[PDB]
Image (cartoon, rainbow, N blue to C red):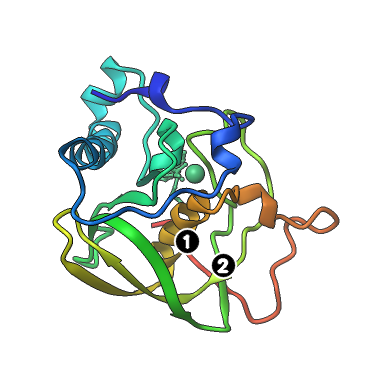
């Protein structure tokens, strides 16, 4: 069972490296790792379990965050009320296309590897199309918008050694870009 002790903190060199592409099929160890990454999110979102193991609630996790420099991510965004939910374990995810229009969460973003909050808007693409493989090597192509698009971009960034605060404007951190879409926290 993965817990906060497995999540490396900001400053660790692995978080700034470029994660390595995965060869398909994945080995048994890599599959178990990806499943455990997803299980971590599940547990983090369970009030009782998260309390018992002092887990910080999260909706996404990238292999580099547990010191594994491989291009694998897990996203677990619960139903927001629209009936839409996102439960994906992706291998070699890549954004193949995206909108020019940007989007951002009004209160900024948080990271499991970053202990203290960092104020500032993180502008990302409002719409993206991702191609990736699933845990069994099959093909997956997602068309995402708004909140989920932001979460997947946050995770993919980890695979390229990019941290959310890298996007924050030094001078005007809370100034939304022209025509950027404000995404309600959901
Ligand atoms: C904008 C991108 C969001 C997805 C990623 C992050 C987790 C992370 O560090 N991934 O690499 C997350 O879940 N962050 C948390 C988060 O913002 N959450 C988790 C559940 C609901 C929501 C609001 O608190 C925080 C509090 C650590
Ligand atoms: Zn993060």
- Which residue is drawn at the image coordinates 30% and 17% (left, top)? 53
Quarter placement of the N terminus = top left
Which residue occupies the foreground of this view, 107 or 129?
A: 129
Is residue 19 toward the left or the right of residue 107 in the image?
left
Q: Quadrant of residue 80?
A: bottom left
- In the displayed structure, 45 sits above or below 177; it is above
- In the displayed structure, 91 sits above or below 3; it is below
Decide: few, some or many residues near mark 2? Use Cα within 10 Å; few <14, some 14-19, many ≥20.
many
Is residue 61 toward the left or the right of residue 14 in the image?
left
Decide: few, some or many residues near mark 1? Use Cα within 10 Å; few <14, some 14-19, many ≥20.
some
- Which residue is drawn at the image coordinates 35% and 25% (left, top)? 55
Q: Residue 26 at what x, y percent from top left? A: 21, 49
- Quadrant assignment for ligand 1: top left
Quarter placement of the C terminus = bottom left
Q: Secondary structure at mark 1?
A: helix
Residue holding disc 2: 124
Which residue occupies the foreground of this view, 4 or 57?
A: 4
Q: Quadrant of residue 146?
A: bottom left
Q: Residue 108 at what x, y percent from top left? A: 59, 52
Is the CB atom of the residue marked by disc 1 within 8 angstroms of ligand 1's nearest atom? yes
Residue holding disc 1: 153
Q: Residue 7 at what x, y percent from top left? A: 43, 28
Task: Please tell me which of labels 1 and 2 falls first in the chain.
Answer: 2
Residue situated furthest top in the rendering: 52
Q: Are marks 1 and 2 in contact (CB under 8 Å)?
A: yes
- Which residue is drawn at the image coordinates 52% and 55% (left, top)? 157
């Amino acid at each position: 069972m993965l817990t906060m002790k497995d999540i490396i903190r900001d400053g660790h060199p692995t978080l700034r490296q470029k994660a390595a592409e995965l060869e398909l099929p994945l080995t048994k160890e890599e599959k178990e790792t990806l499943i455990a990454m997803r299980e971590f999110l599940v547990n983090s979102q369970d009030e009782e379990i998260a309390k018992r193991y002092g887990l910080r609630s999260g909706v996404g996790l990238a292999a580099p965050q547990i010191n594994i420099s491989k291009r694998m991510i897990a996203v677990l965004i619960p139903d927001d009320g629209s009936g839409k939910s996102y439960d994906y374990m992706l291998v070699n995810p890549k954004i193949v296309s995206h909108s020019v229009q940007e989007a951002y969460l009004p209160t900024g973003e948080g990271c499991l590897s970053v202990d203290d909050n960092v104020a500032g808007l993180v502008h990302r693409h409002n719409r993206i199309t991702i191609k990736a493989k699933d845990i069994e090597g099959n093909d997956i192509q997602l068309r995402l918008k708004g909140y989920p698009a932001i979460v997947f971009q946050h995770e993919i960034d980890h695979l390229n050694g990019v941290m959310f605060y890298d996007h924050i404007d030094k001078d005007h951190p809370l100034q939304p870009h022209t025509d950027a879409v404000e995404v309600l926290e959901h």
